Image (cartoon, rainbow, N blue to C red; front, top):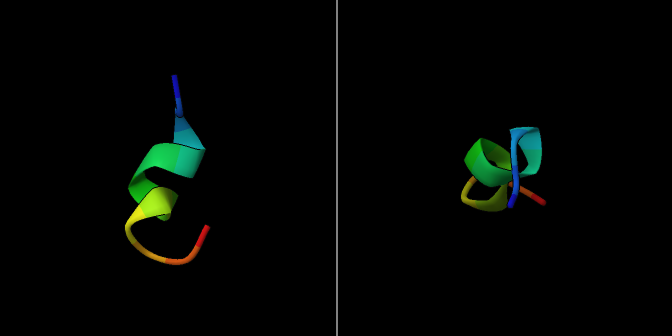
Length: 13
């Protein structure tokens, strides 16, 4: 479960 990498998954990741 992505925490910060989640909102990031859509941004850059």
